[PDB]
């Protein structure tokens, strides 16, 4: 099996697990592969634990990220140290397995890909994409075999419906220069 | 939305994350909800790192787990602290959400349920099950909102092809009382 080409612009929702917190966080996502930008709007279901809701606009072209309190519109601007890393399967990945989620009438077939050298082979980005359309399902990053971060994607709809979602608000002009906490006060 | 009725007998494969270790492990699974028995055969994926493969047979109606070394069939026999908890949606669970996995023209709709409640929004179990079929997709157990374990399921086939998979090997007749590590 060769790697499919993932769509480069879409919007839906995600659930991100982070080792650093032990927790799952939900958000709306806007992924612009064409423009090497991303926007993440934190979503809440349960009111507890108590946390502040943020909006993130990442603009790898301009080497900057903005983080915006969804309520009060406060804005802190920060550097982009990390290099652009798209949601597609890199051409040299290793095919790991293929499986079916669900059952007859409904099911979906996905493939799992990693970066892993047969001669002492282990996997450090692990991507799950659907077979027919190449939609991203899941992305996991591993250090020394242990999960650091894993994101599930869903409710994917193609394209960016309104690119203004990547336009920071006025409040970012005089933006602060360090990350605002999520902790309830 | 009310809770769908998940099939009580099937076999497939799974991938289980554990917060304790931070790692995922693979296995085949045979789930027999009717007879309260589960069989787990650890699947190897790759060396790196090096760990030994067991098979687990869980016979809840007899209060015991067997752990079997796949390379040697050495058996240890372990009392189950566990009480039986089936892979279904408890009638009284809370509806959390419905969403689509995949994308247009290659999509599957699922529902997320928990034992969380409206007034003091707090969980221990969170299942993901398909809307149409009620197949299991994913289970997470959390404490104080933190992930303890999370299992993803796939290649589900209804029924049990060979119920002798639930029958311990004869070596479990002279079982050890104590457990085997992997290294």
Image: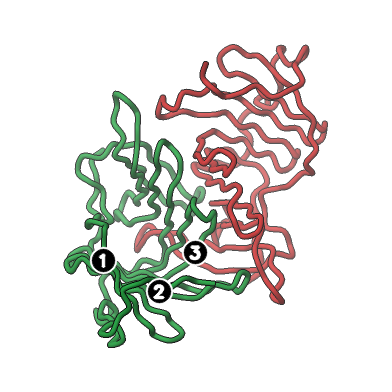
Chain colours: A red, B green
Residue furthest toward the right? A62
Residue closer to the observer: A106 or A181: A181
- Mark 1 vs mark 2: same chain? yes
The residue marked by circle 3 belongs to what chain? B
Q: Against B180, is A146 above or below?
A: above
Q: Residue at x 52, y 56 (%)?
A: B21
Q: Residue at x 49, y 41 (%)?
A: A155
Residue named by callout 1:
B79
Residue named by callout 3:
B25
Disc number at residue B41?
2
Residue closer to the observer: A27 or B124: B124
Q: Against B172, is B22 above or below?
A: above
> Mark 3 or 1 closer to N-term?
3
Find residue B64 and report its image quarter: bottom left
Cα distance in 3D space between marks 3 and 1: 23 Å
x and y percentages locating residue B134 in the rendered image: 29, 53
The residue marked by circle 2 belongs to what chain? B
Graded by Cα atoms within 10 Å as few (under 14), some (14 to 19) or many (20 or more), the crowding at tag 1 reads some
Report the mark closest to the observer, 3 or 1: 1
């Amino acid at each position: 099996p060769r790697p499919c080409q993932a769509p480069q612009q879409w919007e839906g929702r995600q659930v991100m697990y982070q080792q650093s917190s032990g927790r799952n966080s939900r958000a709306l996502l806007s992924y612009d592969g064409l423009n090497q930008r991303v926007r993440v709007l934190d979503e809440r279901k349960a009111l507890i634990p108590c946390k502040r809701l943020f909006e993130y606009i990442l603009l790898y072209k301009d080497g900057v990220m903005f983080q915006i309190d969804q309520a009060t519109k406060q804005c802190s601007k920060m550097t982009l140290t990390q290099p652009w890393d798209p949601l597609d399967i890199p051409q040299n990945s290793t095919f790991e397995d293929q499986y079916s989620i669900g059952g007859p009438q409904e099911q979906i077939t996905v493939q799992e890909w990693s970066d892993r050298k047969s001669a002492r082979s282990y996997e450090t980005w692990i991507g799950i994409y659907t077979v027919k359309d190449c939609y991203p399902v899941q992305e996991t990053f591993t250090i020394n075999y242990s999960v650091i971060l894993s994101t599930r994607f869903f409710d994917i709809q193609l394209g960016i419906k309104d690119p203004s979602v990547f336009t920071p608000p006025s409040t970012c002009q005089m933006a602060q220069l360090e990350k605002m906490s999520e902790d309830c006060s």
